[PDB]
Every structure is written in C-alpha cells, then in structure tokens.
Amino acid sequence: LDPGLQPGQFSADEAGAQLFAQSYQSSAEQVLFQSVAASWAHDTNITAENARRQEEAALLSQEFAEAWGQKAKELYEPIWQQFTDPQLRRIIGAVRTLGSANLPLAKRQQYNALLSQMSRIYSTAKVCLTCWSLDPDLTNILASSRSYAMLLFAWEGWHNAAGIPLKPLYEDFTALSNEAYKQDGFTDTGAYWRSWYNSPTFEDDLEHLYQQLEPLYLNLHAFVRRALHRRYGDRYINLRGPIPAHLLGDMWAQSWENIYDMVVPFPDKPNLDVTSTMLQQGWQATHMFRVAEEFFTSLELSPMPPEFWEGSMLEKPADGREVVCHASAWDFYNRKDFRIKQCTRVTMDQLSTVHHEMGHIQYYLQYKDLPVSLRRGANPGFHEAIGDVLALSVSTPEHLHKIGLLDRVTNDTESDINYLLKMALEKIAFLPFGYLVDQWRWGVFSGRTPPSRYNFDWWYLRTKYQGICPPVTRNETHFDAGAKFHVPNVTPYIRYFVSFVLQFQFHEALCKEAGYEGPLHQCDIYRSTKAGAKLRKVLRAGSSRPWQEVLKDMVGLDALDAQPLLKYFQLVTQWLQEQNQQNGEVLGWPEYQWHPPLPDNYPEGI
Ligand SMILES: *[C@@H]1O[C@H](CO[C@@H]2O[C@@H](C)[C@@H](O)[C@@H](O)[C@@H]2O)[C@@H](O[C@@H]2O[C@H](CO)[C@@H](O[C@@H]3O[C@H](CO)[C@@H](O)[C@H](O)[C@@H]3O)[C@H](O)[C@H]2NC(C)=O)[C@H](O)[C@H]1NC(C)=O
Ligand SMILES: Cc1ccc([C@H]2CC[C@@H](C(=O)O)N2C(=O)CN[C@@H](CCc2ccccc2)C(=O)O)cc1
Ligand SMILES: *[C@@H]1O[C@H](CO)[C@@H](O[C@@H]2O[C@H](CO)[C@@H](O)[C@H](O)[C@H]2NC(C)=O)[C@H](O)[C@H]1NC(C)=O
Ligand SMILES: *[C@@H]1O[C@H](CO[C@@H]2O[C@@H](C)[C@@H](O)[C@@H](O)[C@@H]2O)[C@@H](O)[C@H](O)[C@H]1NC(C)=O
Ligand SMILES: [Cl-]
Ligand SMILES: [Mg+2]
Ligand SMILES: [Zn+2]
C-alpha cells in the first residue's frame, strides 16, 4: 500500500474518528477509482490482460480495506457505537467491515480470480448451431420467436452453456465468501447482505408482503397460461400445471412484456407496445438516453454530465470486442466520472431499462459530495426504484403521446385494462422471481442448499413461486441459477423485490406532490418541479440516515407497504379475477410434477 494511502495515527475518540474518516475519504476515492476504472476496462473489453489488471486493483482495494479496517478496530472498536455523530457511526461501521479483506493473501487472490472467471464465463458464453450470444441473439429469440422448438433450443442452449461451467467456481466462491464475512461476525454472507436493511424482521416482513401480492400473480399466471394454451395447444401447455419456462418472452420468465400481443384483452385499442413505432421512427440508443435525460431535467434534476456522454458505452461494440452487455450504471467515486454500460436495443422495454440505469446515475450525481461510505441508497431497494418510478410516468399512454410514440389517445375502461395488463406483465410477473432468487442464495450461503442440491432447490423455488417448469429435464450437472447474471456476478437480488413494491409507494407520493388528482395509473409527473424536489431530497440523503426515516419523510410511512401497488392495479386485479372465474380456470398449478414433452424431432430441425 502506497504510503500516501496508509492510515496515520488518530485519537481513540470521536474527534479522532472524524479526522480518521476525513483522511480515509481522501485515499478511498483514489483506491475506489482505480478499482472501478480497472473493472470498467475489463467489462468494456474482456481480455485476459484486463482481468489481470482488475484483480491487481481488487487486491489493492483489499489491502487498503485491511489497513484502514484494522486501524478502525484498533482505535474505535468499543466506542464507535456510542458516537454522537450518526453519520460518523455509519462511516466507521462501514470501514470496519473488512469482507474479503479478512481472507489471507492467497485466498484473496483465489477469491478475486473466481469473481473474474465467473464474470468472463457468463458474459462470453455462446450457443452454437456460427454461434449466438445472449445479447442480442438469444434475447431476441426468447422475445419474438413463437416456435416451441426454437425457444427450447435457445433456452436449453443458454442454460447449459452458462450454468454448467460455473458450478465448481460458484461452490468455491461461496465457501471463501462465507469464510471472509464470518470474520466480520456474520453467520454467513447472506446474513451480511440482509443486514443492509437494518430490520430484525426482514424475512418475515417480506413474506407478509408476498402474501398480499401472490393472488395478483396467480390470476395473471392463469390468464396468461390460457392465452399460451390457445397458441401452443394441450400438448405443450397444461392448464393445471406450471408454464414451460421458455414461453414467456424472457430467458428467465421474469418479465412477460414480450408476450403482450398474445394476451392483450382488447386489440382494437391503441397498441401500447411502441417498439414498432420506435423502429419505424428510427430511434437509436442515443435518442433513448436523451429522452430519458430530458425527463430528469423536466423535474429540475441534473442532466447527464459531459463525462457521461464521452465515457459511456451505450451500444454493443461492432469491432466484435467482448463486453459485459448486462446493463449497469457506474460511479467512479471521483465526483466527476459517471457512466452507463449497456448493449442497448431499440425496444420499449429497453427504454425502461435506460430509465432504470439513469436513475442509478441521478442518485450518484445527487450524493457525490457525501463521504464515500454514504454514497449509497438509503437501502439497496431505493437505488433500484428511482428510474423505475420515472418510467411509470413515461409508459402512460398520455406521456407516450407527448413524446410522439402513440398518436391515438383514448380514456376508456378497455384501454385502461390493456394498459394495466401490460404493466402487470412487467411488474406483477416479476414479483415471484424478485423474491425467490435470494431465497435460493441465502440457502446456499447458510448451507441449507449444498452443491448437491443447487438445481433441485433452484427449481423447487421456481415452481413454488413462479409456477414454471423447465422444458427439458434437468439434473445436478446443470446449474441453472448460474445462467442468471446476478449469481456469477455476485449481485444481490432482494433489492429488486423491495424496489418493485417501493416504486409504487414513491409513485403515489410524487403524484400527490405533483397535484395530480386522477387514477394513480394515469399519473405523469413529467415537468413537476415539486415532485422533483421531493425526489431530490431522497437522492441527496444517500445512506446518511436510516431508510425508514427517509421513507417516512417522502411517503408518510416508515415501512414497505403493498397498498400503493394494489391500488395502482386495482382495476385489472378485479378484471383478471372475473375473467378467470368465467373461464373456469384453476388458479395455481396443482399438477406440480408436469413437464412438457420434447418436440418430435428435437433438436434436429433447428
Ligand atoms: C380519464 O378519465 C377518468 C374518469 O373521468 C371521470 O369519469 C368519466 C366517466 C367522466 O364522467 C369524466 O367527466 C370524469 O372526470 C379521469 O379520472 C378523474 O379525474 C378527475 C380530475 O381530472 C377526478 O376529479 C377530481 O377529483 C378530486 C378528488 O379526488 C377533486 O378534488 C377534484 O376537484 C376533481 O373533481 C376524478 O375523481 C377522476 N376519476 C377517477 C375514477 O379517478 C382521468 O383523469 C382521465 N385521465 C386522462 C389521462 O384523461
Ligand atoms: C426494464 C428493466 C428495468 C430494471 C431491470 C432490473 C430489475 C430486474 C433486474 C434484472 O434484469 O434481472 N435488473 C437488472 O439486472 C438491471 N441491471 C442491474 C445491474 C446491477 C449490477 C451491479 C453490480 C455490477 C454489475 C451490475 C441494475 O442496474 O440493477 C431490468 C429491466
Ligand atoms: C482492449 O484491451 C487491450 C488491453 O488488454 C488493449 O490493447 C492495447 O492497445 C493499445 C493501443 O491503444 C496498445 O498500445 C497496447 O499495447 C495494447 N495492450 C495489449 C496488452 O494488447 C486494446 O486496445 C483494447 N481495445 C479497445 C478497443 O479499447
Ligand atoms: C444430466 O444431463 C446430462 C445431459 O442432459 C440429458 O439429456 C437428455 C438426452 C436426457 O437424458 C435428460 O434427461 C438429461 O438431462 C447427461 O449427460 C448426464 O448424464 C445427466 N446426469 C448426470 C448425473 O450428469
Ligand atoms: Cl440487496
Ligand atoms: Mg419487448
Ligand atoms: Zn439497478
């Protein structure tokens, strides 16, 4: 560790802890920048040399974290919890969490190499027939193809190509991660991840939320299953069993927006999937980001700085260079460089992804002047909700008309059901998946799910919550959890379940602040500087204050609450209930053992 980055001496009191955090801040930004920069160089250009530089940068970050983390303990272990400054407590509490820096050098290098290799495997995996990449090739097949056998080839090809080689690495990562955080006092890594929500009843609170939401999913599921049955037939769709996991428009069946055309209740109304209009009009990635930016500035939030436009990767490179295509938003911790890395495609759902990622950036811009340790969301779910809240306004037929994507504008009950059904395919359908992913990982980290049950327990949860089944037989050689980005990239997932609930609480509060007095699902906060000011207060707080208090200041309640989401979807919740009853649907999937047969000539005819 360079001398300038090493901790000096500070008094063993709160006045020295303050000077300690100031000196930490000075060197942490440099260490974070070199680490983020090296990660950027690798993720925008996957080479072996760039992976080596990233592992060396990660090793330096661990060296920094060890020195300052061990100094923080040395000086402040028994007095930091009593400091009068609540932000200083949060800073000290963060610095003294060493994580992977607890591992001995050899195991630090193992750990860093595992993260690098898992990242490379996921983002370079391909399905060969010439070969297809996940983004865009297989993504487009899952989204547009309606051939049961073709969707099967892409689904099976991807899960096999990405998951199988990851499993031995993921086992090793899990053990090292647990070893590291056990030295921080946590029973396992999952316990550390859950501690970010500072709620002793976190898992019970989540279970109570899902109990309120599950009936909406069950009715959406039964309605969609009927629509798929009408297209694929009784051989491939069981009206009393789980839906084959490759037929819902998305590689992970986590968003069903892509099958909207098969489920739209009233096709004679305006087409709310504006993808075809974006293409007809010649939209490109840069247009999508500028339209997103202008919504932010309409609220008097910040535009994207020049450093963002000059540094970001907004399309997949056409030099064929290997990149991490999964969309992400980057804080370089130098208060100047902020970037998005996205292999953007011209679709409506990608426009929503752009808003999601730009919401991450807006957070970074608003709290860039806080101490590095507090440059986070009030909790991780806050960070995930910002852009989605704006996208809720953008997707309204009224707003789409304003930006030229929906010429016809209608306000009738049928159009409302169409819109709420489309929104349910994006938001309700995701809820079981957003909930189950970290249930699986918490069980892996705790040891309830050993490697011998990785896939068994994954598909138990997928069926239990999503009511889907794999369309080909799986076994424990397969590692289908590993075929989902966040698992090999070690990104927690419960934040997305939290965000999908939270964003409707935000939406309701900002709509009220904007002076809107109509149906919640028709609210558009576009150009509301009052709504912008309320949102800005959240963003500028970072993690400096307990999220429960930040939430109460914003929405008037100190807890996650499903009522705004239920209120938003009320009309289609009632409509789906009635339709499924009239159609004599079985809610749920009582034939839980059912899997579809293989196509006659599979995979010969692809
Ligand atoms: C789409 O249309 C709905 C429904 O409009 C209402 O019902 C129709 C059958 C007609 O009779 C309309 O004349 C009638 O407004 C609109 O929702 C309605 O918006 C108005 C405000 O624009 C709401 O009235 C306000 O209500 C608050 C109390 O909540 C009062 O303080 C105000 O003084 C004002 O009266 C009305 O409650 C609301 N109705 C519902 C069911 O929410 C909606 O605005 C419209 N949307 C678009 C995008 O055009
Ligand atoms: C339209 C739309 C909106 C939002 C998403 C979000 C929610 C679902 C989840 C998913 O698609 O499963 N999702 C992402 O994954 C996005 N991308 C990660 C990247 C997080 C990351 C952290 C650290 C390092 C690298 C990446 C991020 O922005 O939160 C999807 C689609
Ligand atoms: C991808 O990364 C490699 C580094 O691993 C880059 O290769 C360097 O390119 C510069 C030219 O600007 C040369 O001077 C270096 O000698 C190269 N280094 C190595 C190890 O080959 C490459 O330029 C990157 N590609 C892009 C498009 O940025
Ligand atoms: C696991 O699965 C591997 C390949 O998948 C198999 O392919 C088709 C033909 C069916 O046999 C299906 O049931 C299988 O999933 C096999 O190579 C492997 O031997 C299977 N079992 C084990 C223990 O690895
Ligand atoms: Cl999280
Ligand atoms: Mg789509
Ligand atoms: Zn996000």
Image: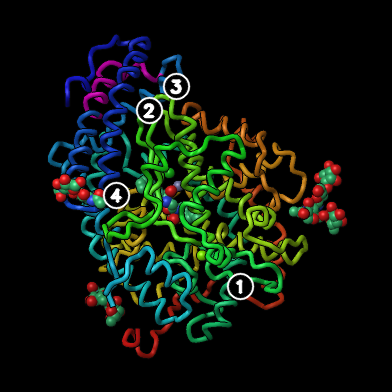
Residue type at the position of mark 3: Gln
Q: Nearer the viewer, mark 4 or mark 3?
A: 4
Q: Which residue is mark 1?
A: 263
Decide which of tag 2 and tag 3 comes sooner along the chain: 3
Does mark 2's beta carbon lie closer than 8 Å to ligand 2? no
**Label 1 lies in ligand 6 vicinity (Cβ under 8 Å):** no
Q: CA distance from mark 3 to mark 1?
A: 50 Å
Disc 2 to disc 4, C-alpha distance: 23 Å
Q: Position of residue 446 (x, y in %)?
A: 33, 48
Measured as percent of width and height from the top left, residue 329 is found at 41, 44
| Amino acid type, callout 1 | Val
Residue in the picture at 31% in, 43% down: 188
* Tag of residue 87: 3
State the residue position of label 2.
372
Camera sees residue 500: yes
Tell me, yes or no, whether the highlighted magenta stretch contains residue 69: yes
Q: Which of labels 3 and 1 is toward the front?
A: 1
Q: Crowdedness of circle 3 by 10 Å Cα count: few (<14), some, many (20+)? A: some
In this view, the residue in front, 388 or 590, is: 388
What is the distance, in whole Å, between disc 4 and disc 1 at their CAs?
37 Å
Left-right relation of 469 to 392: left
